Length: 135
Ligand SMILES: Cc1cc2nc3c(=O)[nH]c(=O)nc-3n(C[C@H](O)[C@H](O)[C@H](O)COP(=O)(O)O)c2cc1C
Image (cartoon, rainbow, N blue to C red; front, side, top):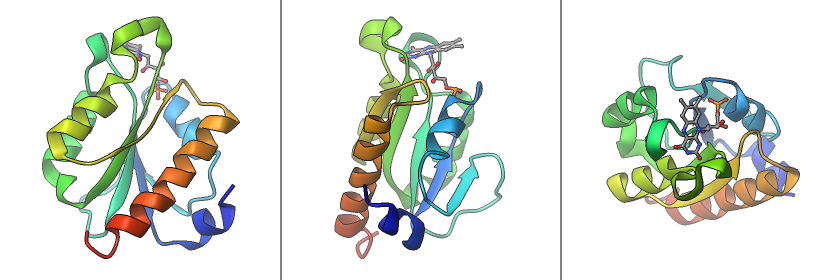
């Protein structure tokens, strides 16, 4: 666990959630700047996106709207899904990754496990270290 980095770094986490699983997931981290895609009218600092998956492995509409406006500051993406969907499992992360040329930080089920939290937070630190100065 890199809780010290999570709680001290200035990295921003922006998420999208409909039934609250993504919300619950990010609340398992120690990141301090956590806001939903719908509660800001501008983004001026680099950020990490955590979203969910809708019909047929699609990116939620609210996330697509957000990205076409602030994808220039996107560092990487993580997506919540459900393996019941097979090949469409958390496909929004793959779509966003290819579309905006950013790395996939993690793909997990529903609210995630402690293992998902660990992998996600470690990847955020790696990408911030590698792309912060650049971004
Ligand atoms: C209409 C609908 C379509 C969904 N489609 C997919 C899908 O294609 N792939 C997947 O992995 N999960 C799919 N899911 C599952 C959600 O991505 C999953 O439950 C997610 O954790 C929900 O996050 P929410 O609380 O953040 O918004 C779907 C759920 C609903 C209600």
